[PDB]
Image (tube, coloured by chain):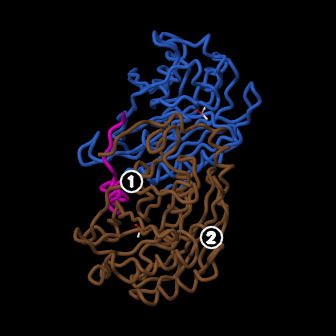
Chain colours: A brown, B blue
Amino acid sequence: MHDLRISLVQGSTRWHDPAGNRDYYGALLEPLAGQSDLVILPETFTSGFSNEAIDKAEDMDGPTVAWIRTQAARLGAAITGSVQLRTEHGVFNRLLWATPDGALQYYDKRHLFRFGNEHLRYAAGRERLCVEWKGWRINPQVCYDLRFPVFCRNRFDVERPGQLDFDLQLFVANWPSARAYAWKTLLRARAIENLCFVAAVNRVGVDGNQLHYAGDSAVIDFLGQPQVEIREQEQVVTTTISAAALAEHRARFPAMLDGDSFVLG
Amino acid sequence: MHDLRISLVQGSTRWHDPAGNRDYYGALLEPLAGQSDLVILPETFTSGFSNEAIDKAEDMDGPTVAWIRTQAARLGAAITGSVQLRTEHGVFNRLLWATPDGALQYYDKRHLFRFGNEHLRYAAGRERLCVEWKGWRINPQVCYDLRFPVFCRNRFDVERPGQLDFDLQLFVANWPSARAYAWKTLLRARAIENLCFVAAVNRVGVDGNQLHYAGDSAVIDFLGQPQVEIREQEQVVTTTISAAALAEHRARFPAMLDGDSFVLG
């Protein structure tokens, strides 16, 4: 495949202000037009990570879904992030995947964040999402999902014949700074054990629940080494990941061949 | 359960010299008598990690198995480490778990080290070993196993009702310093994701094939934070891990309740 340009958009999400966040993140995105293939926003980037946000959650016909589509077209890049989203089946923490070819896919967060009481009224997802963009197969997940290696696992000869399931795994997050060590460590471990790139975006700033966020957004190579890492401040960075290097690593270190078969319940 | 005293025995394994190694590790173990509950030796601590060592591999009736049972009794501690061991099936990389009373359990390395050509002539295991010792449930694994999170997974309400499978996970290894970063990172990630203590022993020195080992043996807490870490030099350290601290963490951060059900194939 070709190389992939990834932009990390490490913003300070405005509390409970969808319109304000569309403007704010829109402004951060503007200079990226034509410069990126994949723009990654934080989890719950329109309201912040909030249980009270459930009662005002938008639906699929709402302004935020329209906005992300608009941004993907405007930038010429895949755009991803999560929003509390209401359906017939409940209100999900829904990762949106919008591509400039006009396609929209989504993934409902499987592991709701029990410690933050997300599980009380939000609905949990089930299926894992893998998408293909610019010849890269990509598995986008959300925040707490990171702590669950079995659901994160890059299987061999399952989704793709004679190949790993995916080339790039993503995490979008509101992961508080008190537990930043776990964030940084797990992201690196996922890249190593799954023989893939990992890209992850976490917000910065302080939220309405008094939580502080240190960012630590990164693109991590298949050796678990961050190619770019940003922290503390509002920041956008765009970096390119090498298809050739990934293919060479997977040939040189064929741990893909030793993985255990399993079936998720 | 009470707190567990764990001794890391970071030795410079003598190349292809079982008798020399029994003497060498024996001498390292002597001062530990009465001071420890669990003594952890490196992987293949009698031969070094070697494909050539398969031809002269000992069997269960051999001096090494006798020696480890003798050490357990002499020290008053469980002793663990692995040895190339011949059976009717072939030659395994067999972790031995020897207790003072003369009991012996074992674990045949499931994932043979493909990059080092271990898989060419050695036989692979299948079963995962969990043992109960001093009220601690313990999962000992071997080297390359560390790269396989599904086989490493601490499941909830499977092996123990309403509890995680184990309290302490161990890795014994010959992990070259060229890839030390992966060793360090993965050990920390396993402790975090599996909400458990992790104890790991890797050799030091240079082997018969001029591969350098940096050690990085450690006892790592359930937050992924080392409590003791040692490197580069031949070194023994004994540390105590807190049962109460583990319980408190599991009560406070209930991630065990969110793990996914799965069945290994």
**Residue pictured at 60% horizontal, 48% vertical:** B184
The amino acid type found where label 2 is placed reads Ser
At horizontal 57% and vertical 55% (from top left) the residue drawn is: A135
Parent chain of label 2: A
Label 2's element? loop
> How far apart are the two marked residues, 1 and 2, measured between alpha carbons?
45 Å
Q: Quadrant of residue A237?
A: bottom right
- x and y percent of residue B120 in the render? 59, 21
The residue stretch that appears in magenta: B247-265
Residue type for callout 1: Leu
Is A59 above or below relative to B87?
below
Residue on which the image places disc 2: A36
Query: Closest to the observer: B138 or A175?
Result: A175
Q: Is residue A175 visible?
A: no
Which chain does tag 1 point to?
Answer: B
Residue B104 position (above or below residue B212): above
- Dot 1 lies on which element? helix
The quadrant in which residue A118 appears is bottom left
Q: Is residue B73 left or right of residue A198?
A: left
Residue A217 locus on image (x, y percent): 57, 69
Q: Is residue B252 magenta?
A: yes
**Residue B160 visible in image:** yes
Q: Are marks 1 and 2 on the same chain?
A: no
Q: Residue at x 58, y 32 (%)?
A: B42
Dot 1 corresponds to which residue? B246
